[PDB]
Amino acid sequence: LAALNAFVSQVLNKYTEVRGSRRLAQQKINECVKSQSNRYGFCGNGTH
Amino acid sequence: LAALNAFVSQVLNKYTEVRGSRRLAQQKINECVKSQSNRYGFCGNGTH
């Protein structure tokens, strides 16, 4: 039972990073695929 | 052995925060050091 608990407590921590990674994916889709953003150092190091 | 496992599981979680902290540093270097960004509330509370 203690072995199962430590695994659950790790899977729950693992799910948290993915939702933080999805915000960046949505932001890039919104800014570089539909709008041609002009912020330096953002998609591509040159002129998008 | 169980004492070592809990320490490894903590060091691995610790390394994950630094990767999220480095993106902000790279963004600030790319935006305020080379481009003079104009977003309010970003580097400095006034006019950069």
Image (cartoon, coloured by chain):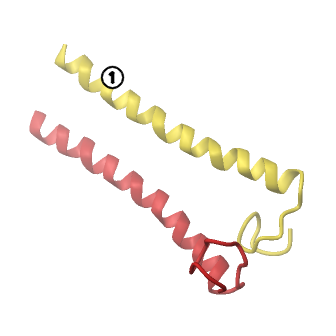
Chain colours: A yellow, B red
Quarter that holds the C terminus of chain B: bottom right
Q: Is residue B1 visible?
A: no
Residue under label 1, please give it: A8
Residue A9 vertical position relative to residue B48 in the rendered view, above or below: above
Residue B16 vertical position relative to residue B38 in the rendered view, above or below: above
Residue A10 vertical position relative to residue B39 in the rendered view, above or below: above
Is residue B36 shown left or right of residue A13? Answer: right
Q: Amino acid at mark 1?
A: Val
Residue B2 vertical position relative to residue B39 in the rendered view, above or below: above
How far from the left and from the top, in percent, is residue A31? 80, 55
How far from the left and from the top, in percent, is residue B8? 23, 45
Quarter that holds the N terminus of chain B: top left
Q: Is residue B18 visible?
A: yes
Is residue B33 shown left or right of residue A10? Answer: right
State the residue in front, A13 or B15: A13
Residue at image position (58%, 78%) is B45
Label 1 sits on a secondary structure element that is helix
Q: Quadrant of residue A13?
A: top left
Residue at image position (72%, 50%) is A27
